[PDB]
Length: 91
DNA sequence: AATAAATGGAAGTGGG
DNA sequence: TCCCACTTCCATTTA
Image 1 (tube, rainbow, N blue to C red):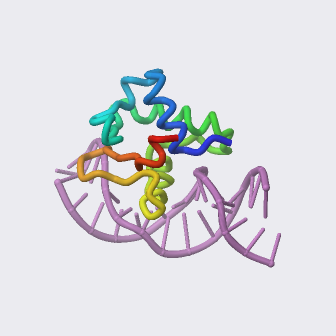
Image 2: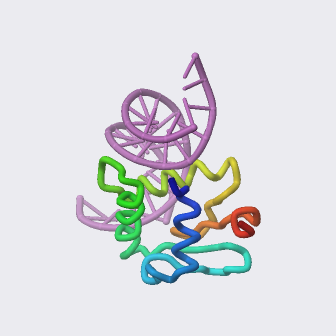
Image 3: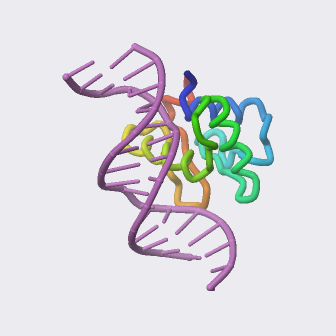
């Protein structure tokens, strides 16, 4: 049962959806979603999870928000931009 | 207004 | 029982 932050890190490693997500500064772990193409990536997350409903970027971003306190992923002050923790990057 | 994004509480679902 | 790790729904706010 893959975790959302790992799904995203795995995508950034593989390059399979390079038009939906990309590194901004990979050394810092900052990454950004495509305004126009993020929904396709959200859809893939829902299908990988086997969720009942179609996944949307908004719901996926709601899940990302919950990582802010524990630290795996923090929202950066640029649109659609986030940052993985050093711990997540190391694994 | 139209569109997009952000904020985030609250309740529901999984699989322990 | 009761937390995990989200998912789903909704109202609101900002640009």
